[PDB]
Image (cartoon, coloured by chain):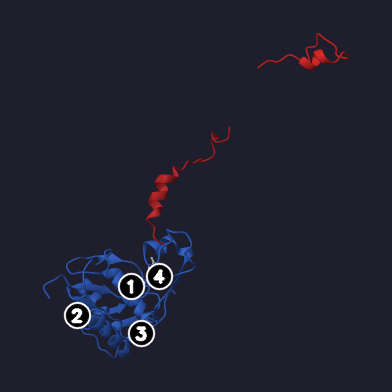
Chain colours: A red, B blue
Amino acid sequence: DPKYADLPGIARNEPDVYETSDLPQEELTSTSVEHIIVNPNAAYDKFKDKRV
Amino acid sequence: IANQPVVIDNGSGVIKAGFAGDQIPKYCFPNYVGRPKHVRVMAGALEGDIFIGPKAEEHRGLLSIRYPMEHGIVKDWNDMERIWQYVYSKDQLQTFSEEHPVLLTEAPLNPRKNRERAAEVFFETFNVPALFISMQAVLSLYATGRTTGVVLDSGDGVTHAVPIYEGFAMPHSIMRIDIAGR
Ligand SMILES: Nc1ncnc2c1ncn2[C@@H]1O[C@H](COP(=O)(O)OP(=O)(O)O)[C@@H](O)[C@H]1O
């Protein structure tokens, strides 16, 4: 802005930025699989005792 | 000794064991030695690995099973002792040698060496105070109640015709062959 006033070869009424418009897995449930979860803390403390 | 006497049904293919009064041997599992076949890696893999019984029949394809009672004669003596310890264990006897009386059975035409070695076990490793090594054919006569009978066993590595007289066979008229279904 002050430099815009300084030099003569400077145009005015310039919205310098012009942008466009702006607006705003499934097989874990598969029937044939025997999908298992673990809770590793429990089984870990369980098998943890296996001093092998 | 004032305890229930142990009865040892020395079956060639299927060995058995039990006590007095009963009609079926208290604990039954055949005669074999199931050595392992792999190497433990995961914590959960059992140890000792020369397993008998549930683990044997269970993991047949994982245990190199062998047979000590070859020709009706045990060859894995020490291992058979441990199989008796397996019987002595919580599984079958839950007791000691020194506690219960024991009764060993035998086939005809047996070498003395086997009987001697067995006695070494029975009174040195095991320490039974009431024990004797009996026969098997006369025991089948006790079962039948007969007197002058011919007993024909049918095992895996033993076959003998025992012409008995009142439970006392002629120890000469008896024939014995050490081969069967094996
Ligand atoms: N139902 C059956 N049919 C045919 N053979 C059998 C049967 N049951 C057991 N056997 C045979 O009998 C054997 C059992 O050995 P066993 O008779 O205990 O030795 P022993 O004659 O010293 O008692 C097995 O090895 C098997 O081959």
Relative to A34, is B116 on the left or the right? left
CA gap between label 1 and label 3 equals 26 Å
Number of the front mark, 2 or 3: 2
Mark 3 — residue? B176
Q: Is residue B153 visible?
A: no
Tell me the SS state at disc 4. Answer: loop
Is the residue marked by circle 4 packed among few (<14), some (14-19), or many (20+) residues within 10 Å? some
State the quadrant of the N terminus of chain A. top right
Tell me the tag on residue B131.
2
Give me the chain letter of mark 3.
B
First of labels 2, 1 by sequence position: 1
Dot 3 and dot 4 residues touching (CB under 8 Å): no
Is the residue marked by circle 1 packed among few (<14), some (14-19), or many (20+) residues within 10 Å? some
Give me the chain letter of mark 4.
B
Q: Residue at x 36, y 72 (%)?
A: B31
Mark 4 — residue? B50
Residue type, label 4: Ile
Please state the quadrant of the image where ligand 1 appears.
Answer: bottom left
Which residue is more in the foreground, B141 or A8? A8
Location of residue B36 with respect to B74 vertically, above or below? above
First of labels 2, 4 by sequence position: 4
Relative to B127, is B177 on the left or the right? right
First of labels 1, 3 by sequence position: 1
Residue type, label 2: Leu
CA gap between label 2 and label 1 equals 18 Å
Which residue, as the protein is rendered here, is positioned at the far front? A6
Mark 1 — residue? B83
- At which x and y percent is residue B50? 40, 70
State the quadrant of the C terminus of chain A. bottom left
Number of the front mark, 2 or 1: 1
CA gap between label 4 and label 1 equals 10 Å
First of labels 2, 3 by sequence position: 2
